[PDB]
Structure formats: structure tokens, C-alpha cells
Amino acid sequence: PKIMKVTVKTPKEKEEFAVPENSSVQQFKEEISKRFKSHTDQLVLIFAGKILKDQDTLSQHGIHDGLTVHLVIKTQNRP
């Protein structure tokens, strides 16, 4: 079993994290925040046309290995 590689497309760049498809949005955006040097509150994930909240899990939206989430970062001071 390989670990699930989730690509995150941001205004800044494009990254890819490794999660055991158990990491929901509340766990996943923490991995984003430390890497992009952003606050988790400044991170809003979007997929299927709707915003992924902490009640949302990436895996439930069909975001598995090779899929990409659309992130919008609102730090301003991290361009």
C-alpha cells in the first residue's frame, strides 16, 4: 500500500503532500500551513465547486492519489 499523494494548487505554486487517505481537511491544511508558512485560518480549500470545511474530508470528495484540490491563501504578506 502506497501513501495517498494529494496535489494542492495554490495562487503561489503547486505542491503535493503524502497522507494515508485518513487525513481530513482539518488535518491536511495543517501540513499546507507549515509548508507555505501561512495560517490555517487563511487557508480555504475548494473542490467540486464548494469550500472544504473541517466537516469535509478530501477522500469523501473523491480526492485520492493523483487528484488536485484548489486552495486559496489569504495571507497577503506570503506572496
Image: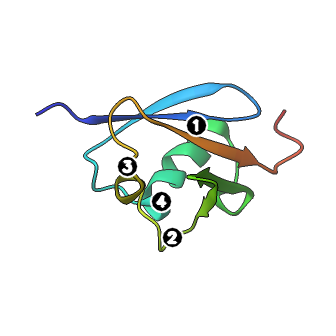
- In which quadrant of the rendered view does residue 70 lie? top right
The amino acid on which the numbered mark 2 sits, given as a three-letter code, is Asp
Whether the residues at callouts 4 and 3 have beta carbons within 8 Å, the answer is: no
Q: Estimate how packed mark 3 is, as few (under 14), some (14 to 19) or many (20 or more) residues with alpha carbons within 10 Å.
A: few
Q: Is residue 7 above or below residue 30?
A: above
The amino acid on which the numbered mark 1 sits, given as a three-letter code, is Arg
Choose the circle earlier in sequence order: 1 or 4. 4
Q: Percent position (x, y) of residue 32? A: 56, 44
Residue 54 badge = 2
Q: CA distance from mark 1 to mark 3?
A: 24 Å
Q: Percent position (x, y) of residue 53? A: 56, 68
The amino acid on which the numbered mark 3 sits, given as a three-letter code, is Gly
Tell me the residue that label 1 is attached to.
Answer: 35
Q: Residue at x 47, y 29 (%)?
A: 16
**Tag nearer the camera, 1 or 3:** 3
Q: Is residue 53 above or below residue 63?
A: below
**Tag nearer the camera, 2 or 3:** 3
The amino acid on which the numbered mark 4 sits, given as a three-letter code, is Val
Q: Residue furthest right?
A: 76
Residue 62 badge = 3
Q: CA distance from mark 4 to mark 3?
A: 13 Å
Give the secondary structure at mark 1. Answer: helix
Q: Residue at x 82, y 38 (%)?
A: 78
Whether the residues at callouts 4 and 2 have beta carbons within 8 Å, the answer is: yes
Q: Percent position (x, y) of residue 66? A: 38, 29
Q: CA distance from mark 1 to mark 2?
A: 19 Å
Choose the circle earlier in sequence order: 4 or 3. 4
